[PDB]
Image 1 (cartoon, rainbow over the protein chains, first blue to last red):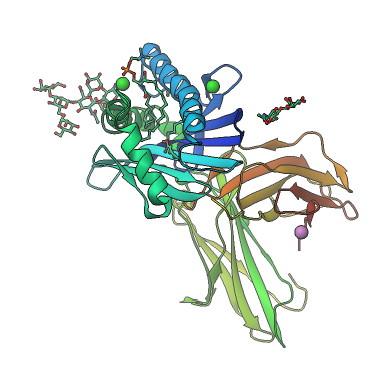
Image 2 (image 1 turned 90 degrees about the vertical axis):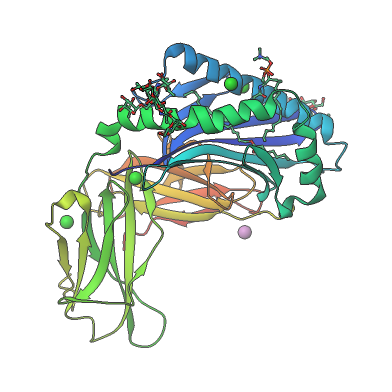
Length: 280
Length: 100
Ligand SMILES: *[C@@H]1O[C@H](CO[C@@H]2O[C@@H](C)[C@@H](O)[C@@H](O)[C@@H]2O)[C@@H](O[C@@H]2O[C@H](CO)[C@@H](O[C@@H]3O[C@H](CO[C@H]4O[C@H](CO)[C@@H](O)[C@H](O)[C@@H]4O)[C@@H](O)[C@H](O[C@H]4O[C@H](CO)[C@@H](O)[C@H](O)[C@@H]4O)[C@@H]3O)[C@H](O)[C@H]2NC(C)=O)[C@H](O[C@@H]2O[C@@H](C)[C@@H](O)[C@@H](O)[C@@H]2O)[C@H]1NC(C)=O
Ligand SMILES: CCCCCCCCCCCCC/C=C\[C@H](O)[C@@H](COP(=O)(O)OCC[N+](C)(C)C)NC(=O)CCCCCCCCCCCCCCC
Ligand SMILES: *[C@@H]1O[C@H](CO)[C@@H](O[C@@H]2O[C@H](CO)[C@@H](O)[C@H](O)[C@H]2NC(C)=O)[C@H](O)[C@H]1NC(C)=O
Ligand SMILES: [Cl-]
Ligand SMILES: [Cl-]
Ligand SMILES: [Cl-]
Ligand SMILES: [Cl-]
Ligand code: NI
């Protein structure tokens, strides 16, 4: 099937000083947000009608309570122990946890934590593993949390028992949006390129869903290996935008075309033709 | 934790720019750290009021990213921009939209 294959929740916890911290969180299917965390209320914001997947309201509420309790206690413990391993304010902690469906059907779970934007720890085999960037501080931290009752057991349950069945339920409940097909549009632009007698041609491709796409500058049926893909950029409302560029000598630009292949097109590729001399 | 990351700022329209035709102006701000950041979309150097944005997310390398956007009708003379302020930036950085 098409569309996202993973669910994850993220945490950004910003510690301004000894007494002030604030946590942002959200839930995601690959890059598509399906949950928000509302710090006004300590509850989740459900962004799609199907964002609860096949979970009952009782179970959703229970998970919300777990997160609400975690978010509050995390800040409490981090502060109490910020004196223990010397940590200078301000600092920021990040966390990502979830699971992913792989080819063959297997579901793999993951949890990673970061401090100041560098890896700090991960959970592997239901055990806390310090990352080498986290230093001795990450070692002391892992040895601490494993002693606090219930934490690792709750983490184990969520990672390996709750997340896999949530992912399967929500991938199915949301399939009409998740596996929809949205045709891109494409257009050409130009502009100066570094060096004498060089031009940069740009094939813009916008509005496609799902994310996998193929864009190539061509000469007839010969793909131009010099094609450079830019990073895929988001549009609002769950579609994407991509620039494919080609550096070409002046006077060798004629004969170039841009071909777009996409799952939504039903084999009707988009082909754009570069014309010279300001004939667009 | 010591090293801060200045934002990358990319401004682009949802559709090819055509004068008179409603469009969407996107500003993608990425690669930055820490997460505190201020982002405005400008019309002729004035802050646009009706601007939406994504909730905070981050890359595999822990760098933050945000998408800000508004509807807009491009014209011949109107100028649009994205203005970012961040602890790595001394003054706010203004990246102009260029339909090319
Ligand atoms: C949300 O959906 C989840 C996925 O549901 C399936 O997929 C979606 C897309 C729809 O198509 C659904 O109709 C469909 O059910 C639900 O989770 C899944 O529930 C099923 C049904 O209970 C469950 O099947 C059982 O699996 C065990 C074996 O599981 C072990 O081994 C497999 C490898 O083989 C491994 O993958 C697992 O992780 C385990 O290690 C099996 O023993 C059971 O057999 C018994 O029951 C069947 C009748 O169903 C009977 O024929 C047998 O003879 C025997 O009695 C049964 O086959 C899936 O394992 C499970 N999948 C996952 C990933 O968890 C989910 O259901 C809820 O969770 C379940 C774990 C279970 O407690 C259910 O009773 C719950 O309702 C559903 N709802 C929620 C809230 O999560
Ligand atoms: C490895 C990273 C974890 C390190 C974080 C450490 C700082 C701890 C701050 C939280 C303090 C928690 C308070 C103490 C115990 C909590 O109650 C305990 C358990 O309670 P217990 O049954 O033992 O006692 C009864 C209490 N209740 C009566 C209250 C249930 N709960 C917790 O610690 C929460 C665990 C946090 C898990 C974080 C996310 C894990 C992965 C998520 C994967 C997503 C899949 C979900 C699908 C939607
Ligand atoms: C931590 O930071 C907060 C701001 O985020 C500080 O709050 C200010 O505190 C001063 C001193 O008491 C007050 O005069 C201000 O009115 C507060 N501002 C706000 C917006 O609340 C807080 O005091 C800091 N704590 C410590 C221990 O330094
Ligand atoms: Cl996708
Ligand atoms: Cl909260
Ligand atoms: Cl639990
Ligand atoms: Cl087209
Ligand atoms: Ni500067």
